[PDB]
Amino acid sequence: ILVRKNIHSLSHHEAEELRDALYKLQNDESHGGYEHIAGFHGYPNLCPEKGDEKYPCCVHGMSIFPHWHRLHTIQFERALKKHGSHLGIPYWDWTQTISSLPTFFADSGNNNPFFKYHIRSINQDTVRDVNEAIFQQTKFGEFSSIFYLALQALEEDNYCDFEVQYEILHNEVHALIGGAEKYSMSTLEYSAFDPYFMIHHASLDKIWIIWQELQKRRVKPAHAGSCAGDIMHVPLHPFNYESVNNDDFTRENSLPNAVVDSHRFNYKYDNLNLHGHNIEELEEVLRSLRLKSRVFAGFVLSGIRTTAVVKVYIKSGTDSDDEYAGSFVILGGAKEMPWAYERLYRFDITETVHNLNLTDDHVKFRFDLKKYDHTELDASVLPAPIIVRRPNNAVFDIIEIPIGKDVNLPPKVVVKRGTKIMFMSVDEAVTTPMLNLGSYTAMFKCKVPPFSFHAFELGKMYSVESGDYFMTASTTELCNDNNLRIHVHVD
Amino acid sequence: ILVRKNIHSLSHHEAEELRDALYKLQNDESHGGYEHIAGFHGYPNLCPEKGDEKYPCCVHGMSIFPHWHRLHTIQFERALKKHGSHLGIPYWDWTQTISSLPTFFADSGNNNPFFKYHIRSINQDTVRDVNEAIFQQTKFGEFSSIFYLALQALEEDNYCDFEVQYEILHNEVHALIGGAEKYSMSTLEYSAFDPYFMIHHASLDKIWIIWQELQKRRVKPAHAGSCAGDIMHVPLHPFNYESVNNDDFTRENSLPNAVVDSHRFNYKYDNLNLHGHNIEELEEVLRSLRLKSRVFAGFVLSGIRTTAVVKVYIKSGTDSDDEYAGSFVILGGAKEMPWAYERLYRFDITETVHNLNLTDDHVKFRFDLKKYDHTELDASVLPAPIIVRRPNNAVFDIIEIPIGKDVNLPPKVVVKRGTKIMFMSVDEAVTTPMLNLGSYTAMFKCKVPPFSFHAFELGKMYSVESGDYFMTASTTELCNDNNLRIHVHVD
Ligand SMILES: [Cu+2]
Ligand SMILES: [Cu+2]
Ligand SMILES: [Cu+2]
Ligand SMILES: [Cu+2]
């Protein structure tokens, strides 16, 4: 019987309840206190039952990334109501044209509890190094910045391929807000303490909702167990571990398959509209993208044990003229629990490609540069972008063009039974054999037969069948000249 | 309405029909001829629809190894009846004490069509280099040689862990019969032509049958799709390809899930007794093994693109005194289609170990020597034996002790939900951390967290839970000092 009203439709009278509730919680050091709730995600680490090895309970990159967050956000909200609340956590639609940071934060003075919070555990206040994060261009379709990504998440079908777009989209915000500060909102291991953090995740949660049932309207209900669900059949840590917020709902309903439905944790949003668009209205904008063929840059991101950014630079035919193809962010931090996107990260680079006039399957590759919160780091681990072209009219097929030679990436799962696959003949040195489904992981360690062309993967081709595939080098030796062994998988 | 009567209970009158039927087939060069039927398995290769790359349709090592064979044997039999037969293909129980090779073969003179056959395609007659393959010791339990293996196949539960024991057992015979001859019955790429071959596989088929329903008597019905079945949902090549024996039954019922039941291809055996033991009687002998703890030497055999033998030598405490721990055979041949046992190969070495007095989990390893049809070959690719101890009373649990350092093998699947696992602390240089379930294949490529001991795998321990596991080196560097990354799996 609670509701997360918009932070914009907020009223002075309403504003009070929020500040009072949060303050009372902030000055609370009990297991249900604010210094303890923010401790779940960032530092200090806990989860493992006395493993004396710490461990960030923050679940990022995993298939349940949104599941652990959706429950944590309600944990924050529930803790408030218990401390004297009236309305739910205010959400902020940061997709729309941002003219300035919410006055709910900016009001640093008057000791606003929503702008920052004193860690208390190891001192240090929650500081933020705001970034531009603005520059209008055009709304209502083709909205530059944020919105596109968010709208590109609802666009995606299936949940496992959606989760990626869901996270990456939310990864952006964290950066601009926390900037490059020590214990900022961008620093995974501390971003949890920030007042915004607790409420920001709610803003993202709302997007999940709109998409959740949005799928139902496409005879493609995706929510609980769909694809990589073996990871879901396990309670969210440390919500289940005996030392949680002790909130009957959380401590027990910590199971991912239970947190899948929001109408269970007693709370609803004032609306289900994004960027001023209603579900039916917004569903139209989505139809716009699908009406225009766009080339995407596949990414098989993997845990870099740290949060940072990455500027995608497209090579030009001139001589080397780079190009700001865009830029995304990867959350994380040393001591984080290992993760690796099983699914590809749909990233649009359409226009950028058309400028230098290159083909998706034809000789097309680029060299991007990544960067930590502030300093430069090993841009090495790309891992080799896996170009993917999504045809316009008549979609939900998507083509997948891996590569041939100098490719770098573990088994990529484009999933979405019915998807198309191919290979990049990049580098003429290597022809177009590329074994195919060698056999099982064992064989995948490169052990191709004596010229016995176990055909299946040729030049510019395609697929349609599902199941478990694979792609190894034409010959045994031509395998170790780049480690060609991308184990593609379906479903 | 046909029957495969024993080759021993055979009578002169009956013998004729068999010789006539086979002869008429042998001198038949049509698509349903004998030179064409034997062509399905060995050379010349076919299967792929005009891939001009040949391809041995012989399916060995795969989970459907017995499925493709069971259908081929009926193909041979059906071809005969169509050419004038009366009884089914005679089976020979080679498990029992062998006093001498069947007189159905030995009768070289009189131009016996069952002793050999002229390839005709590329000349050369079917020759065999018989091996001793005898030496009585004791029957009715603990029968040295053959029978043990066969009885060790019915012993095993589940079908995927059975198929291995099923093949390896049948792999033996091939050797002794073909010996070390060019186009012998031991040479995969030609063994198909041999008259025995066509009938021998029928002998093995009978064992599959007795085991098939034998399981049903243990409330554990395993036949069609059980474990690795994705490989079954595909017709057996080239039985389906348009150019098969054109036998309505084969050409159509080529689907593995259909060949699972024999009572479908119109044919039954004169009995279902092995080594003179009835199903109920034999089921007792099985109860004997389970009543005595036996240590086994796990094996994750993988396609060596050739058929050969391997002598397991156990190291002694003396100084290096080896020991004839036994010996098995691996069928195959250059140009063969890639295979790799997903499941482990149960091989008993009990007594051998007790002599030098060593412990399964404790410092225990051995160096075996493998050999091609006649010459020595790279004994390299072991791959590191994965010792497994099967406790007596109260079985169907099996313990799995992999290893720590200098281990070599892809993801091993002990399956059998409820199985136990551990690790060999062999080599004190490496302690007992061994990460555990790092994450997904991506993470498995070694990328363990910063000392963050994602506990699960410790010293002499165990398991019980199912699902997909894994085991990586304690530290990132300690991983590449042997490539510790055996991806264990259950179910
Ligand atoms: Cu987080
Ligand atoms: Cu977050
Ligand atoms: Cu065979
Ligand atoms: Cu065989």
Image (cartoon, coloured by chain):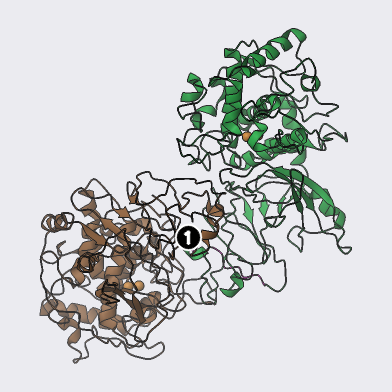
Chain colours: A brown, B green
For this view, does A196 lie left or right of residue B386? Answer: left
Residue toward you, A278 or B244:
B244
Residue at the extreme top of the image, as rendered:
B13
Decide whether residue B432 is among the magenta residues.
yes
Residue toward you, A201 or B48:
B48
Seen at 14% across and 77% down, the residue is A98
Decide whether residue B50 is among the magenta residues.
no
Residue toward you, B419 or A228:
A228
The relative height of residue B98 versus residue A391 in the rendered view (above or below) is above
The relative height of residue B405 versus residue B466 in the rendered view (above or below) is below
Q: Which residue is mark 1?
A: A484
Seen at 76% across and 39% down, the residue is B180
Q: Position of residue B125 (x, y in %)?
A: 71, 27
The relative height of residue B71 versus residue A75 in the rendered view (above or below) is above
Q: Position of residue B80 (x, y in %)?
A: 61, 16
Ligand 2 shown in quarter: bottom left
Q: Which chain letter matches label 1?
A: A
Quarter of the rendering occupied by the N terminus of chain A: bottom left
Visible in this render: residue A81? no
Visible in this render: residue B83? yes
Residue toward you, B321 or B317:
B321
Span highlighted in magenta in the image: B431-441
Identify the secondary structure beneath mark 1: loop
Q: Position of residue B406 (x, y in %)?
A: 68, 65
For this view, does B409 lie left or right of residue A356? Answer: right
Seen at 52% across and 48% down, the residue is A439
Q: Magenta part mainly helix, strand or loop?
A: loop
Res B318 quadrant in image: bottom right
For this view, does A183 lie left or right of residue A335? Answer: left
Q: Amino acid at mark 1?
A: Leu
